[PDB]
Length: 191
Length: 191
Ligand SMILES: Nc1ncnc2c1ncn2[C@@H]1O[C@H](COP(=O)(O)OP(=O)(O)NP(=O)(O)O)[C@@H](O)[C@H]1O
Ligand SMILES: Nc1ncnc2c1ncn2[C@@H]1O[C@H](COP(=O)(O)OP(=O)(O)NP(=O)(O)O)[C@@H](O)[C@H]1O
Ligand SMILES: Nc1ncnc2c1ncn2[C@@H]1O[C@H](COP(=O)(O)OS(=O)(=O)O)[C@@H](O)[C@H]1O
Ligand SMILES: Nc1ncnc2c1ncn2[C@@H]1O[C@H](COP(=O)(O)OS(=O)(=O)O)[C@@H](O)[C@H]1O
Ligand SMILES: [Mg+2]
Ligand SMILES: [Mg+2]
Image (cartoon, rainbow over all chains, first blue to last red; front, side):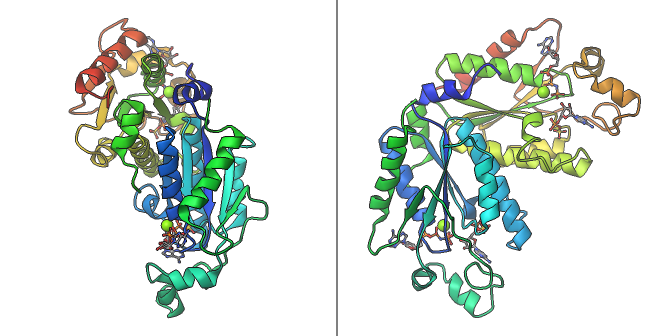
């Protein structure tokens, strides 16, 4: 069709992209995604969050947490994120996405530069002390099998664009500011 | 997150929705989708087309044309369309989507009013005379098994919002005008 990605970007005055937020359960991915969305919205930029929990109740309602289903979960989210980026949207994906090979495949779906991998670099011990949903304790007690960071591996990014949360008391707002500053400098916040 | 669908709609000055375009192969779904997108873009509205062929090369690259895979194809497209609508986008889905039960399930995913079913009411004989890709002839010759309208059923909508193409020489532009007029009157082209 005659309407191109650059036409949609011209309309929105921004560049479509994927902000891929990965990290252990409890590392603060969703909290960061919200803070970022709020901040970008106030600057007049259009974002949309694909959160692992949300998507697992709709598009991915058929997927379990077996390793193969985690890969399919990530794969589908990567493809949908690509569609949002093509629509000119700043798409924020917030999924544990534990496997390096699967996150890398999502990156390869996109043109160089359009995929910003954001690592919530928060150690297991801190996530487990947070344990907002009580999942780690259920996992430790064997009620949840194959839980990421306990009985299934989490593979951190080797070369991500942004690493967050390493240090203490860095607030979700300050972290979103760092992401927004990065996007602004890279030119994603204007056509 | 604090940013709501109504906030995104306020930013874009339009209402998110799904325009579900269904019909036989060759009925002119993609041609209509493009014309519509072009017309809405010129009015400053943001649309995005989910075309069956396109999506089958990415998100749905794992699906065949067996009946169960057509249902899954439609199901996933409905879920993605819902996400686009929630982002405030006018999402145009252009898929054969032959099964009534599966299109109806996509409709039920959305709030009343947010799903506009558009039937390309073009008889098999006309689609087959067009046969732009030579698919009908391959189907007739047994090279393609289970082809919609030949060896697999197409179930027309019983109560769609818009029916197009019934009559001769109605142009894609005139048809898009009818859809745009409908969207405009229903209030989808303003926040
Ligand atoms: N920057 C932060 N500093 C301190 N606490 C935080 C921070 N961000 C999030 N939290 C808290 O840590 C808990 C988990 O955050 P959350 O954003 O839900 O994690 P997640 O990575 O989205 N979890 P999951 O959905 O299971 O993968 C929440 O209760 C937050 O309040
Ligand atoms: N309104 C129209 N009037 C006359 N011819 C048309 C019209 N719309 C489309 N066509 C032609 O019919 C052919 C098929 O149109 P197309 O939009 O590709 O069909 P479709 O429903 O998208 N096919 P498919 O992708 O296999 O499901 C094209 O070559 C068009 O040129
Ligand atoms: N075995 C598990 N491992 C990790 N998260 C789980 C598990 N079981 C349920 N969950 C829940 O599902 C959410 C994670 O889903 P995803 O982000 O979609 O995971 S992913 O690995 O497939 O990317 C977590 O919030 C967690 O609450
Ligand atoms: N057996 C088939 N029936 C219909 N379309 C087919 C078939 N095999 C290949 N195709 C192609 O795939 C396209 C249709 O895909 P979809 O729109 O995604 O179909 S759907 O039934 O699953 O909704 C058509 O353009 C057609 O070219
Ligand atoms: Mg979360
Ligand atoms: Mg088509």
